[PDB]
Amino acid sequence: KQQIGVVGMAVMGRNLALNIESRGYTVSVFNRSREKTEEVIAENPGKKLVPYYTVQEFVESLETPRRILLMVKAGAGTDSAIDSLKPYLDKGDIIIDGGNTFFQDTIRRNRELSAEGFNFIGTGVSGGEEGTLKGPSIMPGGQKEAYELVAPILKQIAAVAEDGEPCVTYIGADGAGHYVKMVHNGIEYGDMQLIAEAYALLKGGLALSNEELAQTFTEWNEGELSSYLIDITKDIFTKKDEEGKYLVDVILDEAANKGTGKWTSQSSLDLGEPLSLITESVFARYISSLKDQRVAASKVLSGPQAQPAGDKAEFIEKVRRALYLGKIVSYAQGFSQLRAASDEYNWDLNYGEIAKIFRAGCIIRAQFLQKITDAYAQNAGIANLLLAPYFKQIADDYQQALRDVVAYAVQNGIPVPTFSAAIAYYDSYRSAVLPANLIQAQRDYFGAHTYKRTDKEGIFHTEWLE
Amino acid sequence: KQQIGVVGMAVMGRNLALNIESRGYTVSVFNRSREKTEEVIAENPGKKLVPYYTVQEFVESLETPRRILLMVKAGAGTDSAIDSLKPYLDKGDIIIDGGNTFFQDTIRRNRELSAEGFNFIGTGVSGGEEGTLKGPSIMPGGQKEAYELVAPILKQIAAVAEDGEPCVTYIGADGAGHYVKMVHNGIEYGDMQLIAEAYALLKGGLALSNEELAQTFTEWNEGELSSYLIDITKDIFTKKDEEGKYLVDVILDEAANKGTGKWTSQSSLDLGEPLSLITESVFARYISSLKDQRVAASKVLSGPQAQPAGDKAEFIEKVRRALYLGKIVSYAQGFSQLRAASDEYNWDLNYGEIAKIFRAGCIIRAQFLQKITDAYAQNAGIANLLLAPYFKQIADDYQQALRDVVAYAVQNGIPVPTFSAAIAYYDSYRSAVLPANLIQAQRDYFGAHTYKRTDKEGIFHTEWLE
């Protein structure tokens, strides 16, 4: 019998099944309809993929306890796939949902399937089509015993960091994996928006051509900013269409989204976390969708004439620094939310291990994730990444560049929502005292909400008039 | 019989009942327990308040169709109050929930009570304890026919604008009123945070004493910033405790919240609205709660030495301008969300009328709300308040001040999350082209998400490598 089965032969499931096959495992494959399953085998002769055309047969062909990988698109189809499998499962079998599922849904299915005798692993899978085929970052949450059973296969198919550690680990119970996958995506939204601002600043302040953009990103990619996102960005700036037009310059600036970005921010608001940078990233996507409103407004609203930033190399460097410190702030906010979530949902998350599996496979992969790993390696209970020696030092050295870039952008009409968010956060966090004293005073005045005092114990209320 | 009854004799309900009484109406009062009801009458001899100590009697003493005002604290008690009333109601009776209820709960009760033959009006009430007693802004949503029946009383007790129009109006169906009340609160969070930044900037850049702060706010209050929030703020800066200490300087800077701020932002994220300013206001409150983390971080993280802002009067004026334009941006974002919500929930909101009832009674009351009223008076379908002639002109004239203040703040270590949000929004909105073209290009690259072109119809996907 096969050790594992994959349900859902669309690209992602097909690729994952091929990945499993490449590691020397024989895998059973199944798809709601039979055409995709037939195409997979047609296109992959000689591979150890065994097709089934009925749920029952697919389930029977797996060694127990069964390990069933659902790669169908997250949503109702996940439930129908589960419902179609149930009647044929033995107590102890394991269903693993690799869809981009909202964590509360995974928590619900996990609790419900558990009550019926089945294990449920909600797992994030990150890497794009090519990543799923070659080695994605895998983020499983669910029963530990079910994880350990399937872990050997997950480890073989995941991307491997350069220290030899596979990019999968036991994240936690029930919905922890899908919650971490959501946060990865929120963090990804933040990195793309920071990069988009770097681009606007170079193009706006120095009028760099696309070839100079490509060259600049290429250089940044050789240093500490080294990352997958930076790499594809330099590629993007060198792409020309069939008639020699730079593709990036004619792509409609309407950034689409698929919830996860929204989801992370909504969670930050439920958990009391100041996740301003990723949240501003989501809002920047929302405003780019108001394209018609923006063109209209551009003919009506006035603004300053953007003046050249000055020496090219120096400005480019300040923008590089700003970007890197911007990422530091965004991730400090992201990992602080992972802690808030861990507490709320009782997951005992291991932040260092999560950072470790983000080092390769996933879309946000970068040498930067090793810096985060090191930070937790030296102090697991660190309150905020900004306090880590490495990050503290980068802030010491790069904040002036961030401050200069934001002032330039604001004085020149270039919107820098996340760079502005990053400096506002850095300055708020290091403030022993914020103006919330006035906010509290106003609340007690118009709403008798009471306040506390810095010089005296007790809870007070004041008759502000007399 | 009495024309109306009030349930819930805590302060807010007591005051509302007294308000109704002051207008010449006799009102029946009731409270779950009898002590508060006994105290109300004890303390208010000669007033036309008729106490009842059983639900049944309270319901019987009202002329039909009955108008029952629930002033109990929003939550489970609202449901228990409703459940206790039901058995004694006649089809057509009207229950009005004046609690600070989340709009989806009002939609649920409205639908459910409707199916049983009863009308349900979820209504925001804003004014604080003193406002509920003297004249609050009232924002009712529910069956129109039920609204018209009770409207005469609501109009008599609401605050009245100087043009003689009472600050209550039919907002819309089901949960529209409570949704508008939520947005008022989100907008209030934004105004308090903008004011808190003005304060940080004056105190940080010019080291103004509290007496100078008071004097400055007093002057601002005499001009276009004229508002309730600005007024109590100047009061706050002159308040001294029993031993001569300025109260504002010893109040613990940990801004509490009660959801509505959070709620507005969560809705903006569900509706695709870039409500960055109020959202940053909520996050600023979240970070002020991390007081211990902030004190710790203040001894560890470095930052620049804040240098004096320069001439006092000139800087003060730039900060006044910045604040006013900041409010313009926040409200543009708020009213755009009111439209997004109106569309989503099928309310056909009348923005001008909502602005009109915010002119007095409510916490955000200000001459500014008349500017918004005028804007809708001249163009009901205006896409964004920034496009309104009055606001367009203020932006033309005050943006440079906003830009100078933010650059100064950022170069000097003073966190200005909302002022930064305001300029980032103004600059994004007027941008015919944003860097989301790159974001779209990256998405198609790693996720094959496809993109559109500015120079060609169709939806494309590109093999970015080759």
Image: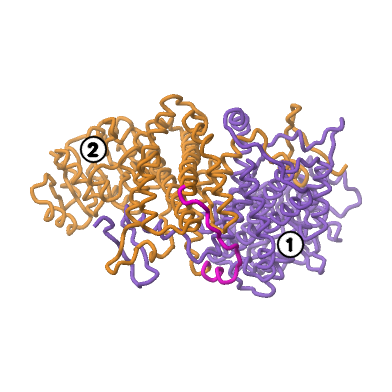
Chain colours: A orange, B purple
- Asked if residue A110 shows in the view, the reply is no
Q: Which residues are magenta?
A: A294-313
For residue A225, which quarter of the picture?
top left
Please indicate whether residue A172 sits to the left or right of residue B132 in the image.
Answer: left
Whether the residues at callouts 2 and 1 have beta carbons within 8 Å, the answer is: no
User: Label 1 lies in what chain?
Assistant: B
Which element is circle 2 on?
loop
Which amino acid, by three-letter code, is at mark 2? Answer: Asp
Give the residue at the far right of this rendering. Answer: B46
Residue A302 belongs to the span the image colors magenta? yes
Which quadrant of the figure contains the N terminus of chain A? top left
Residue B389 picture location, percent across and down:
67, 71
Location of residue A346 with respect to A256 vertically, above or below: above
Q: Residue at x 39, y 64 (%)?
A: A249
Q: Of residues A53 and A69, which is closer to you in this image?
A: A69
The residue indicated by pointer 1 is B368
Question: Dot 1 lies on which element?
Answer: helix
Asked if the magenta segment contains residue A354, the reply would be no
Indicate the quadrant where residue B42 lies. Answer: top right
Quarter in which the C terminus of chain A is drawn: top right
Vertical side of A359 occupied by B179: above or below: below
Which residue lies under the disc numbered 2? A90
